[PDB]
Amino acid sequence: LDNLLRPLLATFSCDCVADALILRVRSELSGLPFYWNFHCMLASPSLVSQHLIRPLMGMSLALQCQVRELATLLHMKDLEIQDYQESGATLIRDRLKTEPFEENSFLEQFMIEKLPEACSIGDGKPFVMNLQDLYMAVTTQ
Amino acid sequence: MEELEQGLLMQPWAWLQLAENSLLAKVFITKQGYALLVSDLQQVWHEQVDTSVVSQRAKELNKRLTAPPAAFLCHLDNLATFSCDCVADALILRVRSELSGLPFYWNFHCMLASPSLVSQHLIRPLMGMSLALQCQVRELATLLHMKDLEIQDYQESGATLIRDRLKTEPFEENSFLEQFMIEKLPEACSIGDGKPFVMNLQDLYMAVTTQ
Amino acid sequence: MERKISRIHLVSEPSITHFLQVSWEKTLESGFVITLTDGHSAWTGTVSESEISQEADDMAMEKGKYVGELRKALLSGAGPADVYTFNFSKESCYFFFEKNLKDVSFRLGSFNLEKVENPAEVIRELICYCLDTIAENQAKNEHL
Image (cartoon, rainbow over all chains, first blue to last red):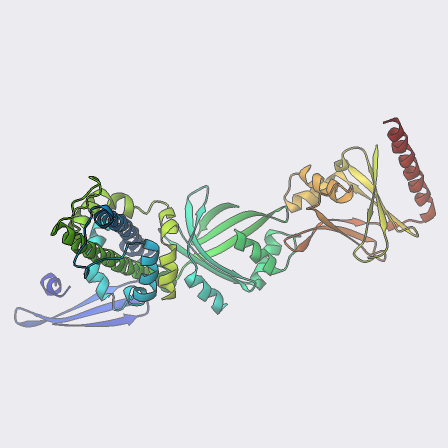
């Protein structure tokens, strides 16, 4: 079961009976076909808090701190290009001039233009690819 | 009442100072009734109420202190001393306020929220927020990379720095995570009492729910 | 002993000025006698120590603080923020009073009045005390 699931995280099927989820495995072990059913109840509010709500909230806070630290980083790069143009008495190839960063306008452009797809839950797919190394870290912490 | 639920999905979370702990609460009030979702960051609780329940429960809690339902609701919209018990899983939230120069009582009869509303009001929004915040990190990291291409053009033709304290190191995202994870993550991911959540994330909460 | 005359309007009777007279022994809290009149008829009743207690204790307020509300309502002790409301059927002789804020009225208390049998006579007594109270404060004014 472990060696079957590790690469994938054979065939599977998913059936609900009242509150309970059954996950069915058809595969092979020793050339022979192998069959399993997982029998899952609804997770308790403890588990959902510990595995989902709390870590997901702790990730959003830490990511908000990332955005803050990247905004102070951005402004510190804007003081630096200013110090070149304004007093460091020089120019560039022009094709690379960036706009001065302001997080108010960064957020308003982000939230009109990019939010519709960015917060897409979808298949949960992109959460497992983009966010897991943060998830493991937040949970440890 | 369907519009009360719809308002609720898109209301932000407030933070409540009990004597006993704190709570997080999102509420939507109209003249029609209210809907409320509460959490202590371990559990979640729900109530929805129309004006029929308002004038009955207010006449019980406040025997001869008469009003139309909508005037009580209007005052709760102002939002006092909070206490609670979990009795079974009624988080009964007991709210003392001052209205009309008189002490007032409301008790919220909050049952364990359904897993479906926990999904719609927390998990899905909170996920959607983490993905959106990560796209903001991604766009600040492209913006930081773009400003380095700009600054490296200066470094590649003349252009010395004057103020000997304005230097930036070249932005690199893996190492910015590495330092954050040791120096910043302990504090920043701490849930605490949920005041960090209500203080800085409610705009994104409101946006992601409306998306 | 103290008394206090106060002029009011019943909600029932916009254009008739009524007179509320209260009379008691310094604490209103000990119980009081209460008269209403409109210059043609009069009504009376009484309130006691345990009745004010029970009225407060059902409303869940410190007695003395509730007595504050009573002084303000019944003895003209209202501030500009305070708006009191006065209601009476002469037919049932049921008095009640209310305070208004949060755009609604809130009952503060109720009385059984009885119509008084000797109307013009308690009116006589009342206007005697008023003519005295003019003359007394007028005499104090001249001196000052």
